[PDB]
Amino acid sequence: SGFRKMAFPSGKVEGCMVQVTCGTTTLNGLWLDDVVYCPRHVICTSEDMLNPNYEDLLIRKSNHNFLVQAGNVQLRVIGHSMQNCVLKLKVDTANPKTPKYKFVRIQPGQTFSVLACYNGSPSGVYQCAMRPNFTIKGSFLNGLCGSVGFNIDYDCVSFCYMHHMELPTGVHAGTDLEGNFYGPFVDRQTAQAAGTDTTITVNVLAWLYAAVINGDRWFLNRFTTTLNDFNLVAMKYNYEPLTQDHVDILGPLSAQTGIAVLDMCASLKELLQNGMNGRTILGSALLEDEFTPFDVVRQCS
Amino acid sequence: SGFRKMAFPSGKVEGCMVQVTCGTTTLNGLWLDDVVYCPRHVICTSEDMLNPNYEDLLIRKSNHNFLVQAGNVQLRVIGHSMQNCVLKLKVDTANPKTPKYKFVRIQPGQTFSVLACYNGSPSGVYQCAMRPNFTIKGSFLNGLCGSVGFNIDYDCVSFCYMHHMELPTGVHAGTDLEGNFYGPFVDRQTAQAAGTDTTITVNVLAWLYAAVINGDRWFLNRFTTTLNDFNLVAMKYNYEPLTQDHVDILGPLSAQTGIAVLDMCASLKELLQNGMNGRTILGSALLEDEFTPFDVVRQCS
Image (cartoon, rainbow over all chains, first blue to last red; front, side):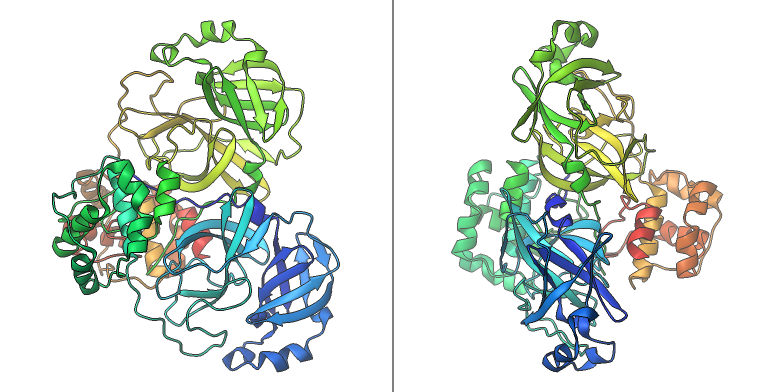
């Protein structure tokens, strides 16, 4: 039938985006209260990025080397500090548009919205997943460093990602808002390998439930299986192993559709082995894994 | 490789969404200056919708039957008026959050962002195309009547769509902001057929250019063709005919990639006839038609 990825409304985040320029390098910053968060690599020349000593580089910089703009306004940097891979630029003006917010570190396979920004100006909003190997796919953040990923729960913006770099493979890597990289990556222009990526099994199951809910059910069979038997097949097709926590997470969708989680696992098992025979599910010719069980519940209920 | 659909930042639209309740029916309204725009079918009972005389129904209603809420605020309806299929509720308070805006009527095959809203509260943002048959696919606006589609150019929000209804097939139908339906549809609960849908040829070509730009070029062949010869094949696979205006529209992408528009048409011709042989283009197993040439230019340049 049809099922679209949905991003959170970006309004609350838009009012926090600023421009941070240092030398010939301009990237995006996040302005929350009297602090502007941005990738520490803003201080690096192209040469510096090859093997930066950030401690030593940061020391040479002065406040007045950091040009922070919010629209047409110029915010004066009062003090600069480094927390892991993120720079914290203290300013004398609290952002009046600061929303209720938390910093959160998300798990692999979870989803969030990214407000893609160029030089402090919002350009667009994307929905994406953190891959099991802690990268983001889609070639949508190229040179848009400092753009942030988030989720909105009630009135609160939970910031979970800040874009730092493209790996040589083109995939995106970044940090949480405390500047800790997702995955084994470092903010240096060197060869770095992402792990083997795997398909997010729980998400694919969620999406199949979505398909049933939307009347697209051709793939449903009258088999069931055990987690153990299913996971043998999963490993073969580079699917993340399915846990009891995952099964527990899928309960509401199982209850809504009257399809036991392990029965849905049996239908996936058959799709993996036989393919889709030139057929589509929710208008897609492949199995989609960037919708969480929560995403499906929110959109389908 | 990878290429994600991007919605416009929704902030400017978020501040315009209101709740309009009439009887047991609650839907979304657009609050611009001292006017609230919403589907006229808000005044209809479930029974009324089967065959409404809107003129007669509107007459029975009074201002005080229209409950208009902006967050926790209650806006008093000063006067109510009907322009085609949209109700215009005059209020005594101008929206202080009114952005620079235009009302525009878009062409079939064009794209826009939809701020999906439930009862005046923004829930999410989607990117979509107006199908050649003047419907919207994706089952994302169900019961979210009054949600609006838009584009943002510079500082200006160009409103182009207001959601009214799902056709019995489940696809979405709606109007421009002057209340003129897109396509042959009416705001009545009766059987209505959408035209045969066709694939948006110019958009598919745009997306192939996108694929080349992102290093995914396996489908490129050393053939060319004429518009006439191509369009013979297109008609066979229910593709929109390609015009010189379309070719002219694709010029910048042709210039960026060094691939003549008619040469790209020849590669599409081959994809249509032979399929994709279990291969993907930009991570998709089918030919995507919801990215305009403009969308591709904005995202890839």
